[PDB]
Amino acid sequence: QSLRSSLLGLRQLLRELPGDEAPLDALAETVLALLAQYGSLRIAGLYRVRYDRTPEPQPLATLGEMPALDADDLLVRTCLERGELVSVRQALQVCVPLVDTDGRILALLAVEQMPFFVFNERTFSLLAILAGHIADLLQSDRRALQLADIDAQRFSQYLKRSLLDARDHGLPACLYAFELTDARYGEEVQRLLEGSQRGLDVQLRLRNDEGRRVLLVLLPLTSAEGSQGYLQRLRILFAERFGQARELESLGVRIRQYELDAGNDRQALGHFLFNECGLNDQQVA
Ligand SMILES: Nc1nc2c(ncn2[C@@H]2O[C@@H]3COP(=O)(O)O[C@H]4[C@@H](O)[C@H](n5cnc6c(=O)[nH]c(N)nc65)O[C@@H]4COP(=O)(O)O[C@H]3[C@H]2O)c(=O)[nH]1
C-alpha cells in the first residue's frame, strides 16, 4: 500500500501542476525524494536523459553532496544502453533509468552512496519498480492530443505497466470484466461501478461482440487477497444501491476475472480480452 500511496501522491501533484512547466523540472525534488526514501539513498542526483539516450550533466536535483556527473562513466553508459538498473555490486554505486511503457528513457537516477546493508536485489527491485511507474506518470495525465480515447490510452498504458510489473518483478494485478446482460439495469450498474473507482484502478467502458456493455476494471499492484476484498466491498455497495434482497448476478452482471501473474504465459491476457470477453484490438492494445 505504501508504493500505491506514494504513486497516488505523485500523480496528484502532476494533476495540479500549472501545465506551464515540464513535470520533470518542477517535480524533480519530489521524484528524487521518493526514490531516496525507497532506496535509503544518501548521495544521489536526478538527471534528464536526452533523445539519444545521453544524460544532461547538470542535475535536476541532488541529495547530499553529489559530485559532478561523469557522462561516460561505465555504470551510466551501461544503464542507458541496457535501459535497466545496473549496480557495481560484489565512483557510482547504482544507476536507475526512468523508462516508460514505450521504452523512452526520461531520466536517470545516479547513486553515489547508499548504506551497504540495502545495497542488494530487494532494494534494486523497489527502485526499478518505482522508476518505471514515475516515468509513466511524467509523460502521463497531461497527454491528450491523440484522437483516440484518453480513457482508452490510459487504460492500456496502465495495463502494459502491470504486465511489466508481473513479468519483471512478480508483482500481482487483477483485471475484472463486468459484462452487463440485462438492459433494464445496465446503465445503473455501470454508473455504480464507475463511482466505485479507487486509487490507481483504471476503468474502460466498452461494448462487446454481442452489443452488451462491458466495464473493464484493472487493479494495479493488487494481490489475490485484495481482489477479493474489492469484490467484497463492491457487493456491499450493490446491496445498498439495489436490493440487499438481490445479488449482483440477479441484475444481469456476469463477472470475468483474470489474474496477472509471472506464471501466466505470453498470449494468456490476449485470450482473456478477445474470444472470451469478446473485445478486440481497437479497444485495448
Ligand atoms: N485495487 C483495489 N483494491 C481494493 C478496492 N477496494 C478494496 N480493495 C481491497 O480490499 C481491502 C479492504 O478494503 P475496505 O473494506 O474498503 O477497507 C479499506 C478501507 O476502509 C480503507 N481504505 C483504503 N483505501 C481507501 C480509499 O482509497 N478510500 C477510502 N475511503 N478508504 C480506503 O482501508 C482499508 C484497507 O484498505 P487496503 O489496505 O487497500 O485493503 C483493501 C484492498 O486490498 C479497490 O477499489 N481497488
Image (cartoon, rainbow, N blue to C red):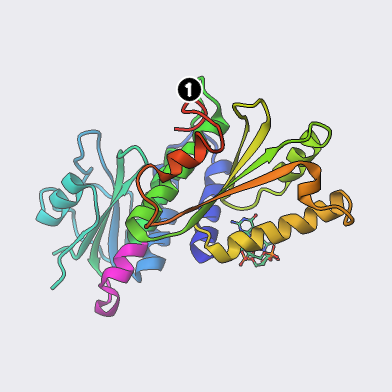
- The residue range painted magenta reads 114-126
Q: Where residue 169 sits in the image (x, y, percent)?
A: 35, 59
Circle 1 SS class = loop
Give the residue pinned by disc 1.
146
Residue 221: give x, y in percent of width and height: 49, 57
Looking at the rendered structure, the number of numbered marks drawn on it comes to: 1
Measuring 38% from the left and 61% from the top, which residue is drawn there?
A: 170
Residue 117: in magenta span? yes
Q: Position of residue 123 (x, y in %)?
A: 32, 69
Residue 185 or residue 172, whichever sits in front? 185
| 10 Å crowding of disc 1: few (<14), some (14-19), many (20+) | few
Above or below, 49 against 262 in this view is above
Q: Residue at x 42, y 43 (%)?
A: 160
Q: Among all residues in the image, which is located at the extreme bottom?
A: 117
Q: Quadrant of residue 225?
A: bottom right
Residue at horizontal 57 percent and vertical 33 percent from the top: 151
Name the image quarter holding the N terminus. bottom right
Locate residue 4, reporting x and y percent: 52, 59
Rendered view: 94 above or below 136: below
Q: Residue at x 37, y 57 (%)?
A: 263
| Residue 233 to residue 285: above or below | below
Label the magenta part by its dominant secondary structure: helix
